[PDB]
Amino acid sequence: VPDATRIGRATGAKAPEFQELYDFDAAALTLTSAVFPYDSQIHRAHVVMLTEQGILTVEESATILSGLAQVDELAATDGSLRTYLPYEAALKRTIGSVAGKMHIGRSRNDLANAGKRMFLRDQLLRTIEAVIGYREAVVHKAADHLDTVMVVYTQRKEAQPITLGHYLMAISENLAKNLDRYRELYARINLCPLGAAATAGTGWPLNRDRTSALLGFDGLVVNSIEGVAGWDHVAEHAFVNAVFLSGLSRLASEIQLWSTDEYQVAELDASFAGTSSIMPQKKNPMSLERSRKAAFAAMGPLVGILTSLNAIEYQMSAARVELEPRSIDALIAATHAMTGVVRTLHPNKERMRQYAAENYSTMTDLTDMLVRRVGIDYREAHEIVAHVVITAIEKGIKANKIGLDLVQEAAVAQTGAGINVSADDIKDALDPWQNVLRREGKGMPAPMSVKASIDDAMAELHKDRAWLANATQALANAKQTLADSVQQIIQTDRKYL
Amino acid sequence: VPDATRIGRATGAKAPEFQELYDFDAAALTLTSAVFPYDSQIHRAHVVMLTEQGILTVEESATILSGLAQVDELAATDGSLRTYLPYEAALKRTIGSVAGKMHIGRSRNDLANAGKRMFLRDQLLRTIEAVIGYREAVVHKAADHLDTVMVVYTQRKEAQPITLGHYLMAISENLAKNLDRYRELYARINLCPLGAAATAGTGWPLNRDRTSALLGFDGLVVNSIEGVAGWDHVAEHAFVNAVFLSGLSRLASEIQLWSTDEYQVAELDASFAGTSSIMPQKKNPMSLERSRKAAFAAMGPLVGILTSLNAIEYQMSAARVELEPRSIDALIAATHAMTGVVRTLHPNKERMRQYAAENYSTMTDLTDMLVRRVGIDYREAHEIVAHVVITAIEKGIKANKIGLDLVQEAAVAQTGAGINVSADDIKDALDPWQNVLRREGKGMPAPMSVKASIDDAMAELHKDRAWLANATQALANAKQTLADSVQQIIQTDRKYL
Amino acid sequence: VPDATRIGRATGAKAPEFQELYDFDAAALTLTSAVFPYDSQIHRAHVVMLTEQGILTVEESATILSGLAQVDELAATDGSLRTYLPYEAALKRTIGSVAGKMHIGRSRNDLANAGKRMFLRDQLLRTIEAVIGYREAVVHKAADHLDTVMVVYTQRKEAQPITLGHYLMAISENLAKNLDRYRELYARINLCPLGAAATAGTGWPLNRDRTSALLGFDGLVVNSIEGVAGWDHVAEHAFVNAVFLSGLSRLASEIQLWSTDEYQVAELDASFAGTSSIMPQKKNPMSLERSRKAAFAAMGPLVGILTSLNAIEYQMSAARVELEPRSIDALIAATHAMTGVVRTLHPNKERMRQYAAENYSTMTDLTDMLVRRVGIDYREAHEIVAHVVITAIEKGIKANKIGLDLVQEAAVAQTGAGINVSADDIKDALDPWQNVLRREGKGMPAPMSVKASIDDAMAELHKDRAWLANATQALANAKQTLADSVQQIIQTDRKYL
Amino acid sequence: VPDATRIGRATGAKAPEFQELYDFDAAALTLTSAVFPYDSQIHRAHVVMLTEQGILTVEESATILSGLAQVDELAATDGSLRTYLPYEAALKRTIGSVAGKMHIGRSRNDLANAGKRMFLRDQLLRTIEAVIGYREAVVHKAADHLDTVMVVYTQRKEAQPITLGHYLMAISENLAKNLDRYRELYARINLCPLGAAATAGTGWPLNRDRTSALLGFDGLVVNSIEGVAGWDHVAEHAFVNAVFLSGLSRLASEIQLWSTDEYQVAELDASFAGTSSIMPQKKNPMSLERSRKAAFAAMGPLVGILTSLNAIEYQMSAARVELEPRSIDALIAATHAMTGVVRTLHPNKERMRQYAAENYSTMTDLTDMLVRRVGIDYREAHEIVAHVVITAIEKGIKANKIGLDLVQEAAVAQTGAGINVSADDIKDALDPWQNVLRREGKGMPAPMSVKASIDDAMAELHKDRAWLANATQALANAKQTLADSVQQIIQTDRKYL
Ligand code: NA
Ligand code: NA
Ligand code: NA
Ligand code: NA
Ligand code: NA
Ligand code: NA
């Protein structure tokens, strides 16, 4: 069956990244279902630690660990077994009363905090990977557009000439700082609260560092109250998502304006646009609007979480609001969609240049030229050039057709006196490519300057990927160590005890 | 005239920190007035840099710089001169048309972004200092309460025995992470966007690193669009304030419950409480409630700022919402108030111990004892002890009066069988101080464990203060370098040119 | 399999209303699935209207309408058919190209706005029914507690004597105003935007009033742009939910404090409490905390929706955030839970009276007595009585043991002079039941006054139920008229054409 | 001194409504200063009522009332006297100890709730007046633009032809519903809580209806707890402000896009635009952006207030967040600014018509014509016309130059067959004015339909003004009755007692 939305101007298939925006809502797991596999890993790590500590015998440990595998299989289709007390009761029905010993020295409170952290930790690495991919698309696109002259806007009005590459490198710098925010957050998420038990620790001689290591954490949440009451990392995860997405909304909005029927300086790839069921002319920026929708929605978890923390004491509380899978899934869909939008965007280079040459964004360079050539102060030069623009608009003279006569008349009308500049001084000031070339300092649009920023960003992206690879491998190594330990116990009991 | 609110049970004067909560609203500056002195520093730094670059002569620079001092004095009483174009026009009226040259290579856009950053930077150091003072009060209070046995709560129900010191060290760990959040933010705030001009840089040969150094920044906002469009640091400052304050609200709420007429396990110092105009019995927790009010209000800037960023393009925009002085002033007042609340809080040690001994928080240790002594699983032990509690409540037996007979009856009623434990096993399990001593692992309430955390926090506080001293001195050194440079130019022109 | 959470002090089963809090998240529909049946009704109403207008023949109409029934059945298990263009394409595959004629004069834009309104309209009646049930439980509980003397709190400190009935009638008045907010909103939700088509109407001669009537709407959204761009009713629905739930959070918090181990003036029914997996003494207020959680979470949709409206133009936009089924489902679960909490709450009448008599809430009446009997001004009387309290606390004298000697000493200590009041004047002022009886004006706790409020609320509840019955019946009558019209067309075509 | 921002293209003076956006922040009162005059009226009304009830003698009443006038004068310059206990103490210093009797039967709690309500009530009438003025400007502008053909947008893409009048009437309908929201809120704000005293009423025999009438309230907040704990009206006021302002942001954004350099279909009046300190070409939409800024900021109070209510019990609490004068002042400034923007907006009628005729918004009418003329279904007609657009864009054919040849080729290319329509059928379908005339139903853009909506809105505006006049006069009559009563008491005591 064909995709019934791909009619008229919506040619071909949706890009996969565009389709993600339509799929995440129905596919999202509940928080309980998303965290359950991590809870199951925690049971194994806790039991292994209790065995190292002599609290459980190897025989008891093996019986429990084999039972966990059986109950996990039951829970794959029976969602009622995905919360703790139901799961423990199924374990007791499966292996007998020794099941209850897996809770020695532990609570649902530290289990819940730890499992949520493991879920958020994996989702944070998923998010960092997606943000790196977005930054890669932005920087790699910029590298092909060092000569793509176009105007930059302030207050939704044409400001001065830049290049598309220069614009994209603003987004790259935004993303670099968001990657810092997320890595900083990761260090706070990746702390283990297990051993806090209910909120006060336990008299059982746990080794909190072992459980933490077996589960891939990089350190402990030390104080036992902080271990169960601490929630600021959840609020912070919601915040970084919201602020990151606000910059994604701003880029989506920018592109939506560029691709209006009236600006027509860029066009979305067909695979990132839809159409209308009634209006056959529509090429609709549905990828952009649904990406913005995700940005706006991300405000919601942030406010709910912070409201809940403002409403309680510094205690474990079941009233705290969570960061849920569907919210993260929306962020990933929007990030992937905007990655593809940027990669595949079609700039209209001729129209971009036309606006830059014709619509008066070159007037700052004309003003700076007067100051530099005749030494007047900036305020008087500005008033002369504003008069040039006013007269040029009234007479229908595009910026690139402004000449010596119009400039002299404005100087006379505004000052009573002419001004000692040549026709060539004016022509060169009004050339939009010369406007770009003259802006050659750090962070400015001249190609040599933008290329310097690209070179720096490519080195930063290498470091971004290395950080992610290291963090991912640390978790994979820990998960394998735990799996090996579980099999050692089960098999040694089966064959030798 | 006496403070008319200090009547009846509101004895003595308000503590100064308590009075701050009443004073900040009327005393707060507008953002324009708060940022204006930083704008004036920017004018000096920009002009000095233009002089180094040969864009201004020393004579022009001296004329401008002396004029800035004159207009600054006018603006001290004439608020109409505290925005840019009015200020520049007053400068022109004061020194002549050369005033206009101070805007060469610059815009209101990069000026505004930089001045706001300098304001927020100083307010961030102010906030870090206040948060350090709060953490100092918390840790120093904890050190005097290693033996102050009391219950910890979960879900507003008595959970297990801890000490007041252990509780306070949860707050210390919360604050350590908030200090990290603020220092991480500082690195993003303390970047200079000057040289971006309108949004695209300039053809004038500025030295962006010099202006940055003269103003105490540690690096540049490199890309010129990011320099004027970037606002994520403002959202992030609002967020860290909100999350930090949510933990302050939680502590205030905790203390408010402790000091209810019904709990009566702590009492506010008289200097942090008020009374009622009608009800003479009231000792009201006004310091706590107004501190929470500031926490709730801090949600507002966070949402407004993020909404504004979600509403625009990746451009300079006058539609962005700001973080305003009154919001930061409220945070500081609440932080100071809670610092004094904690320092001066009066715990009722006898009542705290009574609740711990009598109200069943020791039942976990009774359960753990059964598991440890007779080897039953945790789930069956829990059911026996729950029956002990149910029977004890029905018969009016306080926890510390539970004995061998009641425990054996519960085992029989719930299991048909007695249980092989002694009267001394039970007595020791129900002793709340022994509950504390048994919880001796990392982050647990035993005195040796809490003291370890205190020792660590004292070392961390030394590092917190050193970071703040270094950051403050860097800004002071830069401000003196700028002041010296300005005087060099003015005096050299006056005497030698 | 037993409910594994019902162990220890969590006796019996969860109340059904309590269980609802655990079930709504996994059971919630997506918005697409929730709105789809309303979209299907819209197709029928639009087609019937087109038939009345002569745009479709009866034969074309019958073919389409029979096909809608077939595609609806396919969509019951194939979720891919629950959005418009996929559904229309399935209709074309089922009945042929005439399927396309059902879109004459219509768009996905007016369809979407109308279907969302029909969904929200039904959910608003569901919510009004639940809020009425909550108010019923509150008022009916109050009627049994006109004599249940207890203290009211301000600032979490004991204030003056009231009754439990008086307190509950505050909640009733809150709920009356929330019911007004919801009925006011209903009038704006129950307006039909169909006929706006894309945003500008259509040249086809639709009868917008007929489609509206067939779908149960009470009027039109007149202007075609407002018909597709209008979203304020969605924001308003989110707001009323949030403000209503904030009052529900406040009641839940109040009850949570009453039922602390320290206040112990009320106890939750066992069917509304849980316990701990580790601490056998816990009787945890899980119903209250999860109800508050829903209140906090309701802030999220409100902010996301308003952010999205602040981010766009006055246009149809796919970037607008929606009010989703899971949010409404949470509100209903919390409302039902709190209805059952209130109905089944167990006040400890003796302890309530003890606090009222002993903990100094009667001091206002002692002060008023001095003013009334000896004519001193209120401020001087207040200072004398504050001294009484200070001395009584120091000496360990409960309020009901304060006598003539202590009052005379306070008058002397604070004023140098005794005071001409009798022992009986004091005894009667300190009797907490007399405090209640003396407060006999409108809205005050005396039984005759509270009963007057109950009588008024019972009359209001009758009107609340009548409004709901009328609104529900109007929708049921319209749905039957539409169903009859569809069958008339299908059967007339089958037999007579 | 000239307005230094009026340089270059910022000709003339700022409009007064535009200047309001720059002035409100520094001019705003604190809440304490804004509410103080209402508190002073409450003192008079309470004292008059106590006199009617015989609680105060006429002589005591006269002494108090004359003293209130003296302390009010002191407080005009001494802000320390603007809170209750300081004010009462100044009254005692002025007239003696009888000052204390003005607090008989009252608290700061009911005083505060009532004074805030009187402040919000006046600000709500101020807001309703401003919203009526905005609606007047919108409707009166629409009446001059029934023939101003232009495109409407969906998803920021050109959709179909409408008129500027039709668009403005969408805003009028939005505003009508916001006026309903505000009048509905007024009925809840204008209820008197006085007589609740601390929270439980009083044994003094107050006449709560008299105090209410003297202060202009229309009814009571009956239950005494609701009288002091009730705050939902504050949250609701914040919400209506936020939702109303979101529609104002959307109109501002719409106009900002219309007035881009690229759309250029409208131009702001010079008096509502600014310029740049650096870029002389700028005509910046500063009125629009600062209006949007106010909209975004209005989210903040809404969230803070609701957070505070979610954080407490159903009690009087000093932790509740308030709606502050500066927030309302911002709303009024933005509403006035947008009133002037709309009144003075300059549409470019020729460019609006050009886009409507050339940029393919007429394609729906071409599609509807095929269905109507040859009877094909809507889906097949849509596919043919989409091909027309695709081919026309590729060949550079503007919509109004599409003819029979291009339509037949598209039918053949997409269907293998021609289509039986004439050149005149096509020409008439592509005429944008005929597109408007054909859309003649309720709420559609044809002039006769828009004029019907204007006639209805003019009748509604008459009713809006009558409601406001009645509500205002009721408050003025009450204030005069109170003033007369105060003078009666003072003068009768002076001359006859
Ligand atoms: Na950070
Ligand atoms: Na954290
Ligand atoms: Na930043
Ligand atoms: Na309403
Ligand atoms: Na509405
Ligand atoms: Na209300």
Image (cartoon, coloured by chain):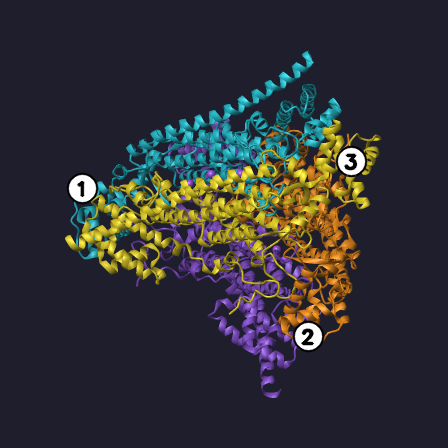
Chain colours: A cyan, B yellow, C orange, D purple
What label does residue A424 carry, if any? Answer: 1
Query: Label 1 is found on which chain of the structure?
Result: A
Callouts 2 and 1 on one subunit: no
| Residue ID for mark 2 | C418
Please say if the residues under marks 3 and 1 sit with CB atoms less than 8 Å apart. no
Q: Residue at x 67, y 49 (%)?
A: B350
Please provide percent x and percent y for residue C255. Answer: 70, 50
Q: Please determine whether, in this image, residue B278 is positioned above or below residue C17.
A: below
Q: Disc 3 versus disc 2: distance between alpha carbons?
A: 59 Å
* Amino acid type indicated by mark 1: Asp
Q: Is residue B486 left or right of residue D157?
A: left
The circle on residue B423 is 3
Q: Is residue B326 left or right of residue A96?
A: left
Q: Amino acid at mark 2?
A: Gly
Residue D200: give x, y in percent of width and height: 69, 63
Q: Nearer the viewer, mark 3 or mark 2?
A: 3
Kind of residue sitting beneath label 3:
Ala
State which chain disc 3 sits on.
Answer: B
Q: Depth-wise, is mark 3 or mark 1 nearer the camera?
A: 3
SS type, badge 2: loop
Residue A65, located in which quarter of the rendered image? top right
